[PDB]
Image (cartoon, each protein chain N blue to C red):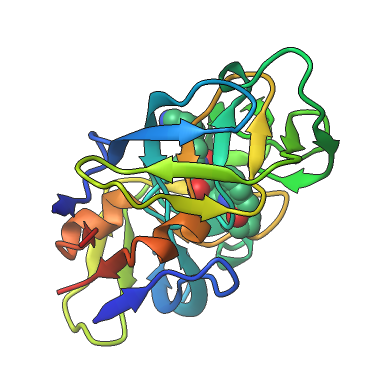
Length: 116
Length: 116
Ligand SMILES: CC(C)(C)NC(=O)[C@@H]1CN(Cc2cccnc2)CCN1C[C@@H](O)C[C@@H](Cc1ccccc1)C(=O)N[C@H]1c2ccccc2C[C@H]1O
């Protein structure tokens, strides 16, 4: 679908996320062309799930803390799609619970940005 | 133009920014559907320009020293376009000199996100 861009209304979407550690869950995620990589909430995971450490570039510079990588791929299903997005790895937000569909996922559903 | 979304290649654009505090300059800016507001480098301004202090949520926790608000509106022109995007106010990166075109600007050029 064509998704209008509005400063007052974030372009969010329902996404079923399978972290392969528990049952697939539906979240509301921000469609973010400015994001190199997808971010999912730590709440999607179980308590015994191992994650890799990392340091990501953010608005406050380097955040050497609340972002981790999954060891296993992450599967994401959009409402109008049966076939899933399969990310080799993606970021996990451990402080807050940000949900961000990055260009890694957007490429897989062949999404484009269009300026008239 | 149609801009493909690619985790390895950021959707950037060359945009002429008029801060109305110095001569208009062309910068490279990230096209970002996840940004509520536009960010421009403080380099485009003069040393005597008054700016407002504020608080902006970003990846690296929560910052309130990084970004400032403009006092005057900002005009942005896209390639081969004479009629300017007019932003009443936008963020000013006083540190890493980021250039981000948010949904405030993307709305005025009628930009859309398209998922096939
Ligand atoms: C993979 C990861 C997500 C960590 N990457 C980023 O953070 C990139 C980095 N570049 C770095 C970069 C900068 C310049 C050139 N190349 C790379 C700048 C662009 N961001 C993506 C941002 O668009 C992320 C969003 C996320 C968000 C939205 C709403 C609420 C919380 C978090 C974001 O930061 N948006 C905020 C935001 C951001 C800018 C301006 C205003 C606002 C308001 C707010 O919406």
